[PDB]
Length: 153
Length: 153
Ligand code: HEM
Ligand code: HEM
Ligand SMILES: [Co+2]
Ligand SMILES: [Co+2]
Ligand SMILES: [Co+2]
Ligand SMILES: [Co+2]
Ligand SMILES: [O]
Ligand SMILES: [O]
Image (cartoon, rainbow over all chains, first blue to last red; front, top):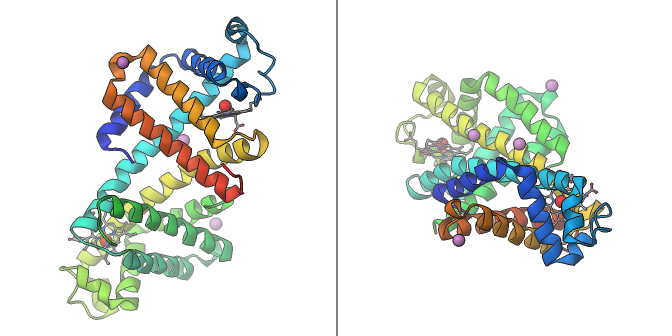
């Protein structure tokens, strides 16, 4: 993925977007629909629109523009924050501590054991299955960063 | 990936962890070191400690347990939050709206054009390359969720 640098560049231009999210939203959708008319056919509420002037006149196209860029902006902001939080952990475990993925499986199993032991009424089979999958996603995230740094975990 | 309920089951049990992070951190490391003694060799400060009674008496071990579960908790709670925004979007766009990944590539191109045209002083070649990579990461995350839902992309 991106550097801390790359993410700040993304978030900086996103700040400009957020100053006029409807204006940006409208332009993005008009640029999409004009460049790739087949995209417009996917929108039951917009596909009647036939001129640039009709698309600009649509109150709801502009509202939908806001909906799209608000959802995306949320996703980019969470991705930047989560990457910046994981990167350091991956880098120390990969470069100084050199913790294989097998060891991360071991501590994952230990966490599942302690939660089962301590919180049975908040950790029956479905909840334990949830946590098992969540810690696997965490290990996969570390693994992916391990390989970018060319460490064999 | 996790269902919406499974992520809440993760958050609910993690609340119980944070209520006594020191105790959980201790029990997790003791379970790791007693279940997998070879993992103890990684820790200069703990690698001499032979028994659970000794491990429980180690203020450094308990201190490290808090650090580990603090780091992991941050990552889990962020992933729970991010996924919960992302999964419904993927679910709606694969199943209800029927939007190919290729179309996500088209709206990404449109976002990059509108940013470059409106904010060139915030969208030089480095910033444009960052945003291009950021939107590819987004589409990759939607394509992963599609594939889980059995949608061809
Ligand atoms: C950056 C990419 C995209 C984002 C962030 C996004 C986000 C949204 C959101 C938040 C909604 C409303 C909630 C929902 O249905 O899930 C929505 C609805 C929808 N999106 Fe997307 N979308 C994107 C791309 C696309 C593309 C490329 C198309 C079509 C070619 C598309 C077609 C639709 C349709 C048809 C709806 C239903 C609209 C209605 O209410 O009539 N989306 N989108
Ligand atoms: C859930 C999994 C894990 C988390 C969240 C985690 C987190 C941390 C954190 C936050 C630190 C301190 C800052 C840093 O150096 O990055 C740390 C240090 C360390 N971790 Fe981990 N860790 C995990 C798994 C493991 C495992 C399985 C091992 C070894 C088997 C390991 C060995 C170490 C070592 C040796 C240090 C340095 C200890 C010191 O000098 O004080 N970690 N870890
Ligand atoms: Co959010
Ligand atoms: Co409960
Ligand atoms: Co955070
Ligand atoms: Co330029
Ligand atoms: O959309
Ligand atoms: O750790």
